[PDB]
Amino acid sequence: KNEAISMLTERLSSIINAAGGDIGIAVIHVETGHTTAIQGTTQLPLYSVFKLPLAIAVLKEIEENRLQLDRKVRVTPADVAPGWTANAAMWRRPIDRTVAQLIEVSIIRSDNTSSDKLLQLVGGPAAVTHRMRALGFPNIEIVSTVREFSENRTRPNTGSAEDLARLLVQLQKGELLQPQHSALLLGFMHRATTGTERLRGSLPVGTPVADKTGTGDAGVVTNDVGIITLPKGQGHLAIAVLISGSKLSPAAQEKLIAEIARAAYDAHVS
Image (spheres, rainbow, N blue to C red):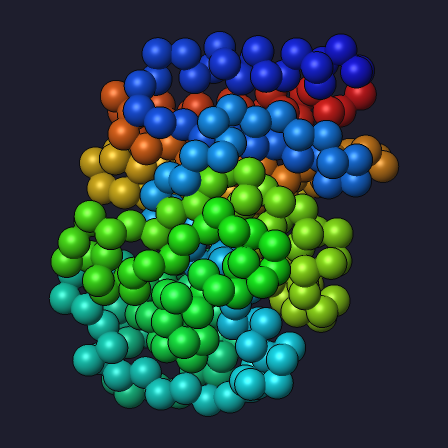
């Protein structure tokens, strides 16, 4: 219905009413461009959502022939920062991982070690930010490595919901990366295992979703960005939801993302 999509802004305002904090939302129908946004231009802390711009920057280095997907990269225990305990069984012993395997674990398990190795291969935070501008996304600011952001939560990587959603629109359309790289990256995002409660939590059974989450400790940030495949031939939705500083419990913030996604789905599906 064209009525449902026109009133989507108002449904989204009710879901987030009284949530406190700063919430950025952008929902873009990929094939038409129809956009619904709330505080969509505000830059908000990304946490592990920044690993999506990072992966695009790495794959663009490969597309400009400064790098190869099958290049072996040595990772060592010194490459693991102190507070990183989530994924440290892969980084016990010196091991070679290809660039593709580093991207894989960076996207799927939100792995901090591989991401910092990737950041060195593209030229650091400033190089990722430069790549974002060159691709048409001037509202994504990568300023810290994962390690730096961990001794100091005052210099976060930031981006706006609209820039992240437009990045995903281009990825899904096939305009952002070579087709085989696009399939590789979307394949990782379909397998991402951290956001069962966010964009996927309230969609109808059988709904394909590619996504990347980000989370700060103790509910200080709850993010999810991704692509929802609509039924039949109704297209795709690119969606970014960034929640910073909300009063709500961590579970209730995840519930807000899930319900936003379902309200957007319902509006765009017949």
